[PDB]
Amino acid sequence: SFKDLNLTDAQKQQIREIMKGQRPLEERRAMHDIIASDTFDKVKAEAQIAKMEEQRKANMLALMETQNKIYNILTPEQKKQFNANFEKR
Amino acid sequence: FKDLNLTDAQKQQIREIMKGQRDQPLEERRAMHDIIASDTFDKVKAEAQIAKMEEQRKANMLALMETQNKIYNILTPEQKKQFNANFEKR
Ligand SMILES: [Cl-]
Ligand SMILES: [Cl-]
Ligand SMILES: [Zn+2]
Ligand SMILES: [Zn+2]
Ligand SMILES: [Zn+2]
Ligand SMILES: [Zn+2]
Ligand SMILES: [Zn+2]
Ligand SMILES: [Zn+2]
Ligand SMILES: [Zn+2]
Ligand SMILES: [Zn+2]
Ligand SMILES: [Zn+2]
Ligand SMILES: [Zn+2]
Ligand SMILES: [Zn+2]
Ligand SMILES: [Zn+2]
Protein backbone atom coordinates (compact mmCIF):
# COMPACT_ATOMS: atom_id res chain seq x y z
CA SER A 1 0.00 0.00 0.00
CA PHE A 2 3.10 2.21 0.19
CA LYS A 3 1.50 3.82 -2.88
CA ASP A 4 -2.18 2.83 -2.39
CA LEU A 5 -3.71 5.92 -0.72
CA ASN A 6 -6.82 6.66 -2.85
CA LEU A 7 -5.12 9.48 -4.81
CA THR A 8 -7.41 12.08 -6.44
CA ASP A 9 -6.82 13.29 -9.99
CA ALA A 10 -5.37 16.55 -8.61
CA GLN A 11 -2.93 14.60 -6.42
CA LYS A 12 -1.79 12.47 -9.34
CA GLN A 13 -1.00 15.64 -11.26
CA GLN A 14 0.70 17.08 -8.17
CA ILE A 15 2.92 14.06 -7.78
CA ARG A 16 3.99 14.53 -11.35
CA GLU A 17 4.77 18.19 -10.83
CA ILE A 18 6.81 16.99 -7.85
CA MET A 19 8.84 14.21 -9.47
CA LYS A 20 9.79 16.53 -12.28
CA GLY A 21 11.00 18.60 -9.33
CA GLN A 22 13.26 15.76 -8.10
CA ARG A 23 14.11 13.46 -11.03
CA PRO A 24 26.23 2.79 -8.74
CA LEU A 25 28.21 0.55 -11.13
CA GLU A 26 31.79 1.71 -10.75
CA GLU A 27 31.01 1.43 -7.04
CA ARG A 28 29.96 -2.22 -7.25
CA ARG A 29 33.08 -2.87 -9.31
CA ALA A 30 35.09 -1.44 -6.41
CA MET A 31 33.26 -3.60 -3.86
CA HIS A 32 33.99 -6.61 -6.04
CA ASP A 33 37.72 -5.90 -5.91
CA ILE A 34 37.58 -5.77 -2.12
CA ILE A 35 35.53 -9.00 -1.80
CA ALA A 36 37.52 -11.03 -4.37
CA SER A 37 40.87 -10.91 -2.60
CA ASP A 38 42.70 -13.33 -0.32
CA THR A 39 42.51 -10.83 2.51
CA PHE A 40 40.02 -8.20 3.66
CA ASP A 41 41.54 -4.72 3.36
CA LYS A 42 39.45 -2.74 5.84
CA VAL A 43 41.16 0.56 5.04
CA LYS A 44 40.49 0.20 1.34
CA ALA A 45 36.93 -0.87 2.07
CA GLU A 46 36.27 2.25 4.15
CA ALA A 47 37.66 4.49 1.40
CA GLN A 48 35.45 2.80 -1.17
CA ILE A 49 32.38 3.08 1.08
CA ALA A 50 33.08 6.80 1.49
CA LYS A 51 33.97 7.69 -2.10
CA MET A 52 30.45 8.45 -3.34
CA GLU A 53 29.15 10.06 -0.12
CA GLU A 54 28.24 13.28 -1.94
CA GLN A 55 26.24 11.66 -4.74
CA ARG A 56 24.50 9.62 -2.05
CA LYS A 57 23.72 12.78 -0.08
CA ALA A 58 22.20 14.56 -3.05
CA ASN A 59 20.21 11.46 -3.96
CA MET A 60 18.78 10.98 -0.46
CA LEU A 61 18.02 14.69 -0.21
CA ALA A 62 15.97 14.58 -3.40
CA LEU A 63 14.05 11.53 -2.25
CA MET A 64 13.32 12.93 1.21
CA GLU A 65 12.19 16.27 -0.29
CA THR A 66 10.00 14.35 -2.72
CA GLN A 67 8.39 12.26 0.02
CA ASN A 68 7.83 15.32 2.20
CA LYS A 69 6.16 17.18 -0.69
CA ILE A 70 3.91 14.18 -1.42
CA TYR A 71 3.08 13.86 2.24
CA ASN A 72 1.93 17.45 2.28
CA ILE A 73 -0.56 17.04 -0.61
CA LEU A 74 -2.41 14.37 1.38
CA THR A 75 -5.65 14.69 3.32
CA PRO A 76 -5.65 13.81 7.04
CA GLU A 77 -7.20 10.43 6.31
CA GLN A 78 -4.44 9.75 3.77
CA LYS A 79 -1.64 11.05 6.01
CA LYS A 80 -2.62 8.55 8.72
CA GLN A 81 -2.50 5.65 6.28
CA PHE A 82 0.90 6.83 4.99
CA ASN A 83 2.24 7.11 8.54
CA ALA A 84 0.81 3.73 9.59
CA ASN A 85 2.50 2.29 6.48
CA PHE A 86 5.71 4.05 7.46
CA GLU A 87 5.64 2.40 10.88
CA LYS A 88 5.25 -1.13 9.48
CA ARG A 89 8.19 -0.92 7.05
CA PHE B 1 23.14 -21.92 -2.89
CA LYS B 2 23.70 -20.27 -6.28
CA ASP B 3 24.77 -23.18 -8.54
CA LEU B 4 28.42 -22.86 -7.45
CA ASN B 5 28.55 -26.63 -6.81
CA LEU B 6 29.03 -25.70 -3.18
CA THR B 7 29.94 -28.88 -1.37
CA ASP B 8 27.93 -29.95 1.65
CA ALA B 9 30.60 -28.72 4.06
CA GLN B 10 31.07 -25.45 2.21
CA LYS B 11 27.33 -25.02 2.81
CA GLN B 12 27.90 -25.29 6.54
CA GLN B 13 31.02 -23.11 6.83
CA ILE B 14 29.01 -20.37 5.10
CA ARG B 15 26.44 -20.64 7.89
CA GLU B 16 29.12 -20.17 10.58
CA ILE B 17 30.41 -17.07 8.77
CA MET B 18 27.00 -15.48 8.29
CA LYS B 19 26.12 -15.80 11.96
CA GLY B 20 29.70 -14.95 12.92
CA GLN B 21 29.73 -11.35 11.70
CA ARG B 22 26.06 -11.19 12.73
CA ASP B 23 27.48 -10.39 16.20
CA GLN B 24 27.43 -6.76 15.06
CA PRO B 25 18.82 -2.96 17.07
CA LEU B 26 20.29 -0.69 14.38
CA GLU B 27 19.28 3.00 14.47
CA GLU B 28 16.15 5.13 14.96
CA ARG B 29 14.61 6.05 11.56
CA ARG B 30 11.95 7.76 13.59
CA ALA B 31 14.02 10.86 12.87
CA MET B 32 13.50 10.37 9.13
CA HIS B 33 9.77 9.93 9.67
CA ASP B 34 9.68 13.28 11.41
CA ILE B 35 11.47 15.00 8.54
CA ILE B 36 9.10 13.64 5.91
CA ALA B 37 5.94 14.16 7.99
CA SER B 38 6.38 17.86 8.62
CA ASP B 39 4.62 20.91 7.21
CA THR B 40 7.91 22.18 5.79
CA PHE B 41 10.99 20.37 4.58
CA ASP B 42 14.03 21.22 6.69
CA LYS B 43 17.07 20.61 4.44
CA VAL B 44 19.60 21.06 7.23
CA LYS B 45 17.92 18.52 9.52
CA ALA B 46 17.54 16.21 6.53
CA GLU B 47 21.27 16.55 5.84
CA ALA B 48 21.99 15.66 9.46
CA GLN B 49 19.79 12.56 9.34
CA ILE B 50 21.64 11.49 6.18
CA ALA B 51 25.04 11.94 7.76
CA LYS B 52 23.99 9.95 10.82
CA MET B 53 22.72 7.20 8.52
CA GLU B 54 26.12 7.12 6.80
CA GLU B 55 27.57 5.65 9.99
CA GLN B 56 25.27 2.65 10.07
CA ARG B 57 25.62 2.25 6.31
CA LYS B 58 29.39 2.06 6.82
CA ALA B 59 28.99 -0.54 9.55
CA ASN B 60 26.68 -2.68 7.48
CA MET B 61 28.69 -2.45 4.28
CA LEU B 62 31.90 -3.34 6.16
CA ALA B 63 30.11 -6.38 7.63
CA LEU B 64 28.60 -7.47 4.32
CA MET B 65 31.88 -7.15 2.41
CA GLU B 66 33.92 -8.90 5.09
CA THR B 67 31.33 -11.70 5.22
CA GLN B 68 31.48 -12.03 1.43
CA ASN B 69 35.29 -11.98 1.46
CA LYS B 70 35.35 -14.84 3.98
CA ILE B 71 32.99 -16.87 1.81
CA TYR B 72 35.08 -16.20 -1.26
CA ASN B 73 38.11 -17.60 0.50
CA ILE B 74 36.55 -20.99 1.29
CA LEU B 75 35.98 -21.57 -2.44
CA THR B 76 38.13 -23.50 -4.91
CA PRO B 77 39.68 -21.66 -7.88
CA GLU B 78 36.86 -22.80 -10.19
CA GLN B 79 34.19 -21.88 -7.65
CA LYS B 80 35.77 -18.45 -7.22
CA LYS B 81 35.37 -18.00 -10.96
CA GLN B 82 31.68 -18.84 -10.95
CA PHE B 83 31.24 -16.68 -7.86
CA ASN B 84 32.85 -13.77 -9.72
CA ALA B 85 30.70 -14.49 -12.79
CA ASN B 86 27.58 -14.60 -10.63
CA PHE B 87 28.60 -11.38 -8.89
CA GLU B 88 28.50 -9.60 -12.28
CA LYS B 89 24.82 -10.49 -12.68
CA ARG B 90 23.42 -8.82 -9.54
CL1 LIG C 1 31.10 -5.82 -10.26
CL1 LIG D 1 9.40 5.44 12.06
ZN1 LIG E 1 -9.97 10.91 -13.45
ZN1 LIG F 1 30.54 5.04 -15.63
ZN1 LIG G 1 32.59 -7.30 -10.91
ZN1 LIG H 1 37.44 -3.78 -10.65
ZN1 LIG I 1 47.89 -12.99 -1.17
ZN1 LIG J 1 37.65 1.90 10.80
ZN1 LIG K 1 33.15 12.31 3.97
ZN1 LIG L 1 28.97 17.38 2.08
ZN1 LIG M 1 14.45 22.01 -3.65
ZN1 LIG N 1 9.67 10.82 15.95
ZN1 LIG O 1 15.96 23.52 10.80
ZN1 LIG P 1 36.51 -9.22 11.42
Image: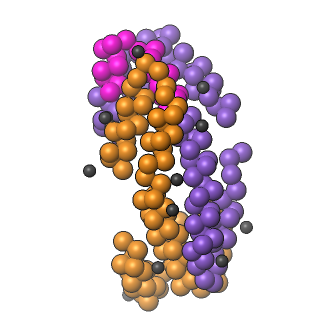
Chain colours: A orange, B purple
Residue at horizontal 43 percent and vertical 11 percent from the top? B7
* The magenta segment: B64-84
> x, y (%) of residue A1?
53, 65
Judged left or right of residue A16, residue A83 is: right
> x, y (%) of residue A4?
50, 71
Residue at horizontal 36 percent and vertical 71 percent from the top? A23
Residue B74 falls inside the magenta stretch: yes
Of B51 and A17, nearer the camera is: B51
Of B69 and A19, nearer the camera is: B69
Is the C terminus of chain B in the top left, top right, bottom left or bottom right quadrant?
top left
Q: Is residue B75 above or below residue A78?
A: above
Question: Image quadrant of residue A37?
Answer: top left
Of B85 and A38, nearer the camera is: A38
Q: Is residue B20 above or below residue A30?
A: above
Judged left or right of residue B77, residue A45 is: right
Can residue B80 be seen from the camera position used here? yes
> x, y (%) of residue A59?
44, 63
Is the N terminus of chain B in the top left, top right, bottom left or bottom right quadrant?
top left
